[PDB]
């Protein structure tokens, strides 16, 4: 039993809700919140901009030190950093950004990172400003993630569209 509330159950392990991931994380304080990161951990917009703003830029400060030490992530890769005031940990995961020409096949690799954590609050990878089809992102999530994932979908039209189209 966990403290996530109001989620629709899609499969044994995947749950979905129309919610603002920032507000959800502040309420639940999950062990892991997933950020829709880029390889440079430059948290400008979308989910990343929102999560970073909610940390008063502490996420960006920590991320800049991480990059200065380790260099960029790989597309499809991840790193674990602090969750600041939002969660115990933040799993920064890089899905392919279609608006940069990156290979959508890497979306499965990106979701594989979730399997290293028993429970996660997460967005749909490569959705929104990363330019992939969200119906496809949800399908890849369900077919790749085996741990317990609570998906927060920003827009109601799409939340409603994803449920009604879910197979
Ligand atoms: O991953 C992309 C996803 N983005 C977010 N998901 C949940 N909460 C969020 N808060 C701020 C951004 C954000 C998204 C899906 C459909 C339409 C637009 C954006
Ligand atoms: Cl977005």
Image (tube, rainbow, N blue to C red):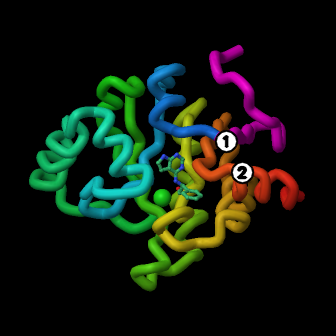
Q: Residue at x 71, y 41 (%)?
A: 16
Q: Residue at x 45, y 72 (%)?
A: 97
Dot 2 falls on a residue whose secondary structure is helix
Q: Which residues are magenta?
A: 1-18
Dot 1 falls on a residue whose secondary structure is strand
Which numbered tag is attached to residue 159? 2
Q: Nearer the viewer, residue 75 or 97?
A: 97
Left or right, 55 with reference to 19: left
Up-down relation of residue 90 to residue 114 (above or below):
above
Q: Is residue 15 magenta?
A: yes
Q: Which quadrant would residue 72 be assigned to in this image?
A: bottom left
Q: Residue at x 74, y 57 (%)?
A: 143
Left or right, 104 with reference to 158: left
On the image, the x and y values in percent for residue 129 come to 47, 67
On the image, the x and y values in percent for residue 103 come to 51, 80
Q: Is residue 100 magenta?
A: no
User: Which residue does the numbered mark 1 point to in the structure image?
Assistant: 18
Badges 2 and 1: C-beta atoms under 8 Å apart? Answer: yes
């Amino acid at each position: 039993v966990n403290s996530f509330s109001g989620y629709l159950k899609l499969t044994d392990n995947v749950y979905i809700k129309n919610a603002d991931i920032v507000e959800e994380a502040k309420k639940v304080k999950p062990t892991v919140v997933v950020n829709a990161a880029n390889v440079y951990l430059k948290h400008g917009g979308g989910v990343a901009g929102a999560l970073n703003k909610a940390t008063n830029n502490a996420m960006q400060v920590e991320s800049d030190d991480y990059i200065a030490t380790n260099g960029p992530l790989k597309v499809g890769g991840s790193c674990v950093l602090s969750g600041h005031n939002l969660a115990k940990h933040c799993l920064h995961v890089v899905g392919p950004n279609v608006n940069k020409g990156e290979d959508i096949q890497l979306l499965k690799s990106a979701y594989e990172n979730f399997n290293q954590h028993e429970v996660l609050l997460a967005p749909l990878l490569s959705a929104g400003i990363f330019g992939a089809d969200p119906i496809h992102s949800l399908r890849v999530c369900v077919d790749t993630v085996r741990t317990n994932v609570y998906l927060a979908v920003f827009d109601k039209n799409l939340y409603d569209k994803l449920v009604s189209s879910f197979l």
